[PDB]
């Protein structure tokens, strides 16, 4: 049942999921306290900088990451590429992220995720998208800012958008919810489920531009359940120290004294791009 | 579920003609002609179109006079979004409420939350997305609607073909594509899938808008509708009683051209109507 | 041998004829006595539909029966475009042809009647060759190349007859390899385009209609290559319907005889005044 | 009928991979990997894209060298509308002509009258209307085509879904509405009705455009194609022979995820391609 | 009389006319079986690539070409440059081509070719242009595609246009021909002459992008009387072999077996440009 997958993702709350491209990065991530590793071909900053078609990683590399760690292993598939997802599931990983950072394979339809046994992550920029991805079978939502820039601005925008719309929905006149669902282009039943629950019906992590402990704690204070870090660790001057600092920031997000400690003398952050 | 019971009650109307009536005399004509139900409203759509002014729910006294004049179901119209007009109609004790676009819209952004009511509702639609939105709000029956008050069937044909055509597309669609299809219709996914599984609308679907002749009514049935509403074509015609009977018989015998000739022969002046083009 | 070919063959019996719109039995008798090859039953002549407005539908079966009883020549009647039930009714009455007519109020803006579903032959209108071939593929056994309705102005009939016949002539010498693209551009079925090329003419009978007001107009349509003419308004909106109807019939029969055209046009009475839309 | 015989020949390629080749070495690699046919052309689509210049039929000498290097059927490309290139190809004795949009268009308004030839033709399409127009001109096989020379499958997915989706719409459609549907497709009505009756394209339909990995090839088959062409994704990759075999296996076993893992594992560098 | 010039050009039917820039190219052309050589400063591909004002060749070079061959010698003059044409005629060559490949000298008027004793070739893209050039005195028409690209697409377009309009005209209602002449902006008398003749009233060769034997045979199968080759020979890897193959293709244009033979192992074709 879908609810089993939704419940599984609850275990990741309070965690940092780290993009890794090889087994060495995966070991760094687990040693730093990541709650899961995300296997992909290149970190988003490199995909942005270099171009080319970005696809699912080779199964051999994913197997190498899978046997190098004991925490959950996720991997990315192109949007709509349900055969990449079939291969990932057959390898025996724990989650598939149908990821907009890879090159879109189907511009009109996402994967029918209910056809799979393992849980899926999907991205969103707004509540309507989040609920559409959930109805397709996403068990976890990544609210996504800019990929590969180190700039948190779009993550802040999109997190505030999703959470703000949920707060509006919570107090809305029931009679107006039908039109709200039409405007969101989202399934009414899921809209009402979100209204009664008072939060997103699945775990919601922030992603996109998280470069510093301060960024990660910010996402948590805005109400996210966790954070993805794609480029900010492995495009930085000291990946291992920075990864641990970000893990600590998510765990202690309301403790300014701790946030000072973990941020102090951390090395060159990812320089990134101001779009 | 209570909604399933309302949906099931409307099944009795299949094969029928629902006639708009403005007084007790028209209601008696409708019943004697064999209508499956009467629809109480202040003025027939052609008169609303010609005269203008704000069109509202009928006075409860007129609705009571109509309800006492007939034994077939009595429906009555309320303005879109005017949930208090609907409360009044339900408290009178009629059988269905039609949240009708022919009356002056009262809420441009929201329809009545029809699930809050005990009696069943009819709503109009022009396409499948609208039909399914109205159903999700609690409509137990759908009126696929063309032009009101013109005697011109062109838009009813267009909208019947649109709704039924989209259902046929949906029936055979790749399951993986239905998510995006629901998004494009701005319709609730679960209802889209239910329509896909059934191969038809989940509730009774009548045609309405410009039905003026027996041929028009039979056309709507051959296009796949479950029945027809006649708003203006009977009481703006030269012989309302005989034309009402002929339209009832056309719906009963919609696949029988010999019968359609018989009931159409020498019917008197039809509603002249208006060609908007 | 095919059912459609038989229908096409029936309409060919009307070559050289004038088909006259009629609204009652008196007009029908006037038409037959004038030499019309057929009468066309409709509620109002096109000039009256234009002037008066209102929704224009199939005539009441009672009136069609009265017309059918009053004449021995073939009886046609009009149905709205797409209104296949009106057509089912007309065929059940027992008339000879149905005209799916743009002069009545369109009932289906996107689809015409599937005319192959009927026993009796259909007439449809067209303004260009692509339209004519589409109507034929739907089952029309006869094409009415149509100008303006109800105005007495032949200008659009000339334009559309010249367009249809001109594209047919373009087909004759066309490189076979270019016909695929020509069919695409016409949005017409390729097999019917090739049949038109092979025949050097429309695969069904082609009459002109629209604004025929004088004998000269009718002979003009015949000299442009049409097989016959419809007269909708120009007879019964004129000052002497009976004499003008005979004159137009004679003009179609003797369209290449200027002396006859003079004789039948002389002292003919007031033509339909009509309207210049320009 | 002569056309039905040609349509029958192309049907024998179902379940296969057709591999673009530019020389006899690539041709041998293709056959040994299990390709169902080779496609002789001057340069693979990715090179045509990166280099520019007018792309034409290959020199007959190169086609003959490919033809005698393999025992599987040999196809070769001709420019759209270049019916003399097609006459020359047929006279060489090859098995199929692909009137190909990857070569430089020679006639912007008209395709080759393929019914005039003895050997079967492949044509590309992006939608059902185009496919049926090509079939009416005499194409015995249809290549539903995405982007050429980029390694990006997105447009092939779009066009395969478009063709297949319109075929599905046609199956349940009110017969009376089919006339207007054929007008809107600018397609011959008889071929529209034949597609409705069959519930599939009246000729074999292969996918092409951006197939770079075994997953891509299996995706095309699960979407309902009869086979795939690979133009650049093999010979612009790090290990053509092993990748060619893996793609053949993926088409043969497209609904077996375990097999798809096995043949995809440790394949080497795919073609990097371009995200337009 | 004009008819003498028109009749002279009939002798070229079935032939290939080859652009040459010096005496060596001219000898190659005649040895390969060209029906005439065309003397110009630079081949169209070089004019396109290099730019600059392209004019009539120096008389000395034209004299060198003239005494190096025994087949007819044509030379090019800029459009409207009637003094260049006067010089060419005084040299004693056989034809002048008033050529759009050279730099236009008069944007509004062509040479009054009836003022000359020797026949002229002019280009066209459509029937109206062809008939205007003929009325000015062109005894031969070059239906012209792209110059200097090796791409036949525009030649195919323009050949199909001219021949297609002639076929339309042949069957047209006589009464409609007046308006057809107006629409073509062509002289009515010449329009009617073309209608009664059923073909162009002068020899019509194709030109523009002919790069392979297949290209040349294609132009002949579309109904041309011959072909010009500007760049496709002397911008190719083996000019002499390719020139002979193209000559054979025009002579045997309906023989696929011959077309295979002459095309087989021909060397690098002109690479050209896809515009």
Image (cartoon, coloured by chain):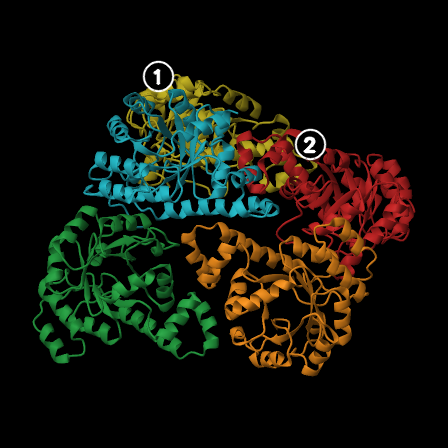
Chain colours: A green, B orange, C red, D cyan, E yellow
**Which residue is under mark 2?**
C2
Q: For residue C55, what is the image quadrant? A: bottom right
Check the residue under mark 1 and report the chain it is in.
Answer: E
Instruction: Provide residue E228's location: percent of width, then percent of height.
Output: 42, 27
Mark pair 2, 1: CA separation: 64 Å
The label number, if any, that marks residue E115 in the structure image: none
Q: Is residue D225 visible?
A: yes
Instruction: Provide residue B119's location: percent of width, then percent of height.
Output: 58, 74
Instruction: Provide residue C231's location: percent of width, then percent of height.
Output: 81, 47
Q: Which residue is more in the foreground, B267 or A228?
A: B267
Task: Name the image quarter holding the N terminus of chain E.
Answer: top right
Tag 2: Cα neighbours inside 10 Å, few (<14), some, or many (≥20)? few
Indicate left or right for D255 with E114 as reference: left
Indicate left or right for E197 with A109 as reference: right
Residue C152 position (above or below residue B138): above
Q: Which residue is more in the foreground, E243 or B22?
A: B22
Q: For residue B94, what is the image quadrant? A: bottom right
Element marked by disc 1: helix
**Which residue is under mark 1?**
E31
Indicate left or right for B161 with B18 as reference: left
Task: Name the image quarter holding the C terminus of chain E.
Answer: top left
Element marked by disc 2: loop
């Amino acid at each position: 049942p879908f609810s089993v997958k939704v419940g599984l993702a609850q275990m990741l709350r309070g965690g940092v999921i780290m993009d890794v491209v090889n087994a060495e990065q995966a070991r760094i991530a687990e040693e730093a306290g990541a709650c899961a590793v995300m296997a992909l071909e290149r970190v988003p900053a490199d995909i942005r900088a270099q171009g080319g078609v970005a696809r699912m990683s080779d199964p051999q590399m994913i197997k190498e990451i899978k046997q190098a760690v004991t925490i959950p292993v996720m991997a990315k598939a192109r949007i709509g590429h349900f055969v990449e997802a079939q291969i990932l599931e057959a390898i025996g990983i724990d989650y598939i992220d149908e990821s907009e950072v890879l090159t879109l394979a189907d511009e009109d339809h996402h994967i029918n995720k209910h056809n799979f046994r393992i849980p899926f992550v999907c991205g969103c920029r707004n509540l309507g998208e989040a609920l559409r991805r959930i109805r397709e079978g996403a068990a976890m939502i990544r609210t996504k800012g800019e990929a590969g820039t180190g700039n948190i601005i779009e993550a802040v925008r999109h997190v505030r958008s999703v959470n703000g719309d949920i707060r509006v929905l919570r107090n809305m006149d029931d009679d107006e919810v039908f039109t709200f669902a039409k405007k969101l282009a989202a399934p009414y039943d899921l809209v009402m489920q979100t209204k009664q629950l008072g939060r997103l019906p699945v775990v919601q992590f922030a992603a996109g531009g998280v470069a510093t402990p301060a960024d990660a704690a910010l996402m948590m204070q805005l109400g996210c359940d966790g954070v993805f870090v794609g480029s900010g660790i492995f495009k930085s001057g000291d990946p291992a120290r920075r990864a641990r600092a970000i893990v600590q920031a998510v765990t202690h997000y309301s403790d300014p004294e701790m946030l000072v400690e973990v941020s102090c003398g951390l090395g060159e952050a990812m320089v990134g791009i101001n779009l």
